Amino acid sequence: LLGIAVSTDYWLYLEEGIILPQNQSTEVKMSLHSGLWRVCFLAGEERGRCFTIEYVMESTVNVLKMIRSATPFPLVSLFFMFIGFILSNIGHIRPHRTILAFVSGIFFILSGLSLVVGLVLYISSINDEMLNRTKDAETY
Amino acid sequence: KKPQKSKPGVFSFLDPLAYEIWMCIVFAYIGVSVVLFLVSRFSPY
Amino acid sequence: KLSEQGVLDKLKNKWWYDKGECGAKDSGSKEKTSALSLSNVAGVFYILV
């Protein structure tokens, strides 16, 4: 599930839009779904850019650059199930000399610890840039 | 720029108590814990 | 002549006061408090983990 999630660039949605006052309700202006490696841009002006973050193109781009600060910890997290499961295969063929299981179970526990660190660095990187927009009443 | 709500620091939870209190808590955390140890030495009952 | 009788001062009262104001009218009742973000309480998790 983490192997599917990292290559997937459908982590988070954004809908940049402008309000409409009365007998008129809403009007979208920009939209993209985001990824940790690279952005695959969406139906904002119908331009299908699977666009790398390291190349440029505002505040929604400032959202996208801060996502890279939470890149390494899921990459740290994916490797620790890679080292956790292969040592689990060793205990199935050769059950004796049982020390390898008790060590590999630590790497299951220490794997998700980086994921909680991974989500804390991720979600706090979303909400501060949610705060960092200048609060204008006309743009929802 | 009109100043907005600032970016919250990573240690923004210990904001409502000043720096000298947080030292005086822990220094009294130790000091009460030391004296509570030395009280129970002299007394069996 | 306009300054000794305050025509220019009234025109100063005219043009900077008629354009709409941004004073206590949006500092008065255009605030509601938000929920806490994660970033307000983020450092507790770093001490925890």
Image (cartoon, grey):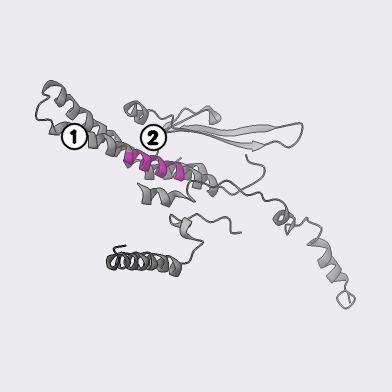
In the structure shown, which secondary structural element does the residue marked by tag 2 occupy?
Answer: strand
- Where residue A99 sits, quadrant-wise, is top left
Disc 1: host chain:
A
Determine the main secondary structure of the stretch shown in magenta: helix
Q: Residue at x 38, y 45 (%)?
A: A69
Using the image, name the chain to which the residue with label 2 belongs: A
Between label 2 and label 1, give the one nearer the viewer.
1
Which amino acid does the dot numbered 1 rest on?
Phe
Q: Which residue corresponds to mark 2?
A: A38
Residue A117 located within the stretch drawn in magenta: yes
Q: Are marks 2 and 1 on the same chain?
A: yes
Q: Foreground: A135 or C43?
A: C43
The image shows residue B37 at horizontal and vertical percentages of: 30, 64
Q: Which residue is mark 1?
A: A102
Picture quadrant of residue A17: top right
In the rendering, at what x and y percent does residue B7 appear? 50, 54
The answer to which of A3 and A14 lies nearer the viewer is A3
> Most extreme residue toward the bottom, as rendered?
C4
| Pick the front one: A124 or A135 | A124
Residue A9 within the magenta-colored segment of the rendering: no
Q: Quadrant of the N terminus of chain C?
A: bottom right
- The magenta region covers A113-124
* Dot 1 crowding, Cα within 10 Å, few <14, some 14–19, many 20+: few
When the figure is inspected, residue A20 is found, relative to residue B18, above or below; the finding is: above
In the displayed structure image, the side of residue B25 where residue A44 appears, left or right: right
Q: Position of residue C13 (x, y in %)?
A: 83, 66
